[PDB]
Length: 223
Ligand SMILES: N=C(N)c1ccc(O[C@H]2CO[C@H]3[C@@H]2OC[C@H]3Oc2ccc(C(=N)N)cc2)cc1
Ligand SMILES: [Ca+2]
Image (cartoon, rainbow, N blue to C red; front, side, top):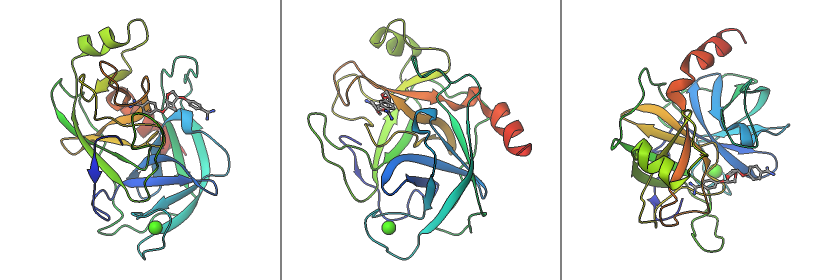
């Protein structure tokens, strides 16, 4: 997260860290047994880390649970990042508490201008690299589809949306991938792509979760 702030320990209780000997992506707890992340975060051998604040220190509220299954969206396209969503099943159900809690799926798509909270342990620099150990947060509004598509002509599909700031300075970034965009108490987005980070007229692009809620629900019910 570039231009954001320290969230505070466990203030984003649905945020998870995907770990394969190291943090490599974020994700969102949508119920005690399942996480939503980005398809581009796919890898084998994932451990889901819940209740995390400092990902390099055991602070006492962590739950480490291995994935039992990954499901990349049937139509994910790695060339264009279209349908950039994946489901991860936890080997054992998370124990829910104040610091480990699920986030609601939406029932409608969000309107331009709605404020959202985006979070993650991604790069905090727009130029160069710096990776933080505690979770960072950013408030960002959903941008008009026309400003989104004009920023990235030919490359935004109706399964994507832009949020952030055209002026730059404030954005998600590498390492935030797969993490949540939560708006009005619902998971409306997943950190997906962008050109660099916090660059002018290049806002973040996010997987439009409202277009996937029936797939999510059908898939989890059948697995
Ligand atoms: N694992 C690989 N080899 C891999 C997978 C995905 C890659 O690139 C895609 C395209 O861009 C995304 C995604 O992962 C890296 C980059 O992460 C972000 C996240 C946020 C923003 C933004 N809000 N400005 C920009 C890029 C590349 C290699
Ligand atoms: Ca920790």
